[PDB]
Image (cartoon, grey):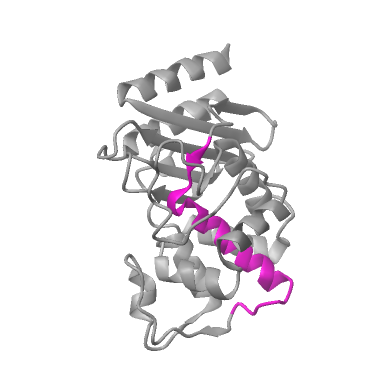
Amino acid sequence: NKSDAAAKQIKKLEEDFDGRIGVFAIDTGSGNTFGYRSDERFPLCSSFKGFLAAAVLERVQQKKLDINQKVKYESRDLEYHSPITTKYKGSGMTLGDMASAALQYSDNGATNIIMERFLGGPEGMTKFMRSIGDNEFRLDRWALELNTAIPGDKRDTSTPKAVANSLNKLALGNVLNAKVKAIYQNWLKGNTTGDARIRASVPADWVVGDKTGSCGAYGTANDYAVIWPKNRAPLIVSIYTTRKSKDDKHSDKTIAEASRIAIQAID
């Protein structure tokens, strides 16, 4: 009945702004879960960038890469929306700083440099996700090309549930060792783009780490988060949205509300 009430409220919210909301939330302490369209496909947009940063950290842990190695790109024509990589073009960036920039600022240069040199491209990114037992995630295209968010299109999608599961395994589980997991957590905690999304749905004193995604088409946007409430086990929240028309703008407030509803549902 608590599940069905949350479902009624997500359905209404999706009808109010004429779109589609997909939700998956986990209370990692009780194991209680809430899902709504949690098995349907949604565009990842930039949200995949948060898993790319984990892929890099896995490599670092395996000693295949060094977190301090200089990554140089002095001749590169930087993709649009490269606020961090554009400042360091002259001097380069450590692999660590570059990976976290991809996460924290959604930096496209950081994203594409890392996928071309370290991760084996979109197929490589997908392979990493298969390796943690995620069978839904697929990345098909590079940083600026995956934003088309065409209805029905399977490229560069996942499901809310698969996103949540993966984040749980990467942020809280055992894919990363203690030291490297802590780094990943701090990266997520210092994300800068998510203030109006999951972050806006919880009390100010709860600690949150997140990665957002905004397609810029079909009002498609999302957020996924690890949340450490005061004196309580962590939560995982995954919220994906699309809208009917190509020209519709995303709704931050819908995502925040969907999050509020999801958090109550597993309470």
Residue at image coords 62%, 34%: 26
Can residue 59 be found in the magenta stretch? yes
Could you tell me residue 223's position as x and y percent?
Answer: 45, 44
Q: Main secondary structure of the magenta part?
A: helix
Where 58 sits versus 192, above or below?
Answer: below
Q: Which quadrant would residue 203 be assigned to in this image?
A: top left
Residue 168: x %, y % from top left: 64, 46
Which quadrant is the C terminus positioned in? top right
Q: Left or right: where does residue 84 sit relative to residue 162?
A: left
Q: Name above or below for residue 67 compared with residue 162.
A: below
Q: Which residues are magenta?
A: 41-67
Q: Report if residue 168 is visible in the image.
A: yes
Q: Residue at x 60, y 64 (%)?
A: 183
Q: Nearer the viewer, residue 209 or 211?
A: 211
Residue 13, horizontal then vertical, whole percent? 37, 23
Furthest toward the left, the residue is 247
In the rendered view, does 224 fall on the left or right side of 120?
A: left
